[PDB]
Structure formats: structure tokens, C-alpha cells
Image (cartoon, rainbow, N blue to C red; front, side):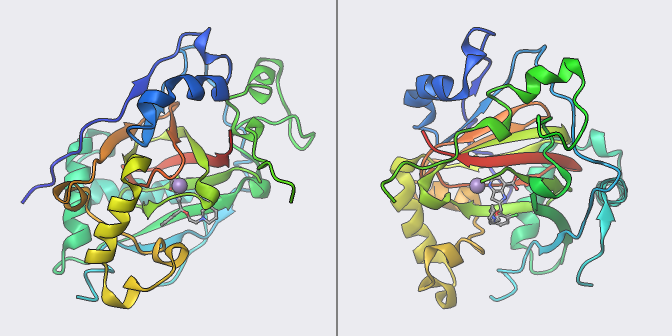
Length: 297
Ligand SMILES: O=C(O)c1ccnc2cc([C@@H](OCCN3CCCCC3)c3ccccc3Cl)[nH]c12
Ligand SMILES: [Mn+2]
């Protein structure tokens, strides 16, 4: 009955020498990490960027997420500040589990998330501050843009190769900016790959962990076949870009069908890299703040 956690994806803890450049580092770990689809990177302990969003004016209208909307086939929106969203998020989680938010084990949130996704008896609705452009209120990383103050001790982070604003994003051919995610408990993203099969890199600036699931690219077609077998018939014929709006699937279902799935809890201050055509999905353990961008090698 209970969710069975997938095996853990690789975690790398590069020394300062190895931490010199994301592209060089990712190229070096690729023989392992491309076989798990996702990996986690823990920066050296002394690498701690300051949070550089304009928190005063940070306002947003999160999207509403009904966990069991797909099983349902078988109000709208409030404006928040970062602060008021956090107060709502913590209240929701502590009320839901009847304990302080930081005392809820990550395995319990995970088990309850997947129970709720398939539950026809309990309708749980959460909110996700998803796809907030970093051009709106700024990146979470400091940038030498002249649109905000950079202290001297923050300049190294504005120039760091691991600053997501400094990733190479142009694709080579003869023929843009990071996105922000303000999470609460159970807010989620369903299974998808990136446009152009790009890499993506994801940084959790602060807050409670983000739980990830990843599938290596050599199993992409197997996952797509399981999806096509088990997706609602009304959605079976949809183009992939539209189907990926609603590709919610319990990782154990994929695993029972022979699809390799790995998991990780991304904690604050840690990066998650997804490799080309590595399907991934996840959910937030609680109030947090993430930044993500696609890049090409
Ligand atoms: O939330 C996270 O931390 C997270 C981590 C890794 N990848 C993703 C992908 C999403 C979202 O993409 C929405 C679609 N936009 C994508 C970027 C801008 C263009 C259109 C998404 C996809 C499915 C269902 C819900 C959500 Cl929010 N969130 C992710
Ligand atoms: Mn993604």
C-alpha cells in the first residue's frame, strides 16, 4: 500500500578545485549521472550566495494544484507576498500533519503526497508560485545588472559560473533567463523533459527540501510507452508538449514496468542537474524558493 522510495540518485560534493566550472564538472560526472538522469551537487561548505530578490515588492499569484485531478476523471487565485505565502504554507503543513513543519519526516510527506495523488476520497488543493520570471523581481542570485546593490562579499557570487544567470543558454545553429519557483508542501511538477532535450540546472536558495524523481535518458522511450499505456485515453493522442502538462505518475508504477527511477531530496544550498532527455518530476516538502534554467553544452 505504502509508497516505496526509489533508490537515491548520485550526490557529488566537489572540492574547491573541482568546483571551478559547472560545464567542466558536469562533463566529468556525466558517465555516472547520465545513467541516473538526475544528480545532486553540494557546493563546498563556504560557498553561500546571498539571496538577492527584491523581497519588498515580491508579489505573485500562484497556480492552484489539485493533487487528485487525474484520478477525478476516473477559489481561483489569491495574490501573495513571499511573507504571506510562507505564512499560508507553514500553516497548511503544520495543520495537515498536526506537528511543527520542521518535524515532519521527508518520507512521511513523500508517502502522503503519493497517497493523496491517487485518493478519490480526500481532495487536497495546494498552490505553487511557479514559473516566476527572474526578470520580474530579480534573480535569487546577485547579478551585476545595476538594478540592485551588490556588496563586495557578494561579487564573487555575481561572477560565479554556478550563478544560474551565468550559464550558457544559446544553442548552436546556422539558424533565456532563470525561472523561479516558490513552493509549499505538496506543490509539484509532473513528468517532463526540457525543450530541445536541454540540460537543466536547479538551485534551492532556501526553505524546506524539494523532492525529485529522475529517469535516465536511455529509458526515455520506455517511460513514454508506460505513459501511453496508462494515460487517460482522452489524453493519449495529445502531443507530448501538451501531454506533459498532466503527466502525473507514481514512480512505483514506472518502476513496476521496468523503468529505472532515482530520487533525491534537494536541500537548501544544493544544485540538481537534469541531463538531456532525462524525464523528471517532483514536489516540495514545504515553503521554499528555487531557481532553474536550461543550458546547452
Ligand atoms: O518546480 C520545480 O522545481 C521544477 C523543477 C524542474 N522542472 C520543472 C518544470 C516545472 C514546471 O514547468 C512549467 C512550464 N514552464 C517551464 C519553464 C518556463 C516555460 C514553461 C511545471 C511542469 C509541470 C507541472 C507543473 C509545473 Cl510548475 N517546474 C519544475
Ligand atoms: Mn524541468
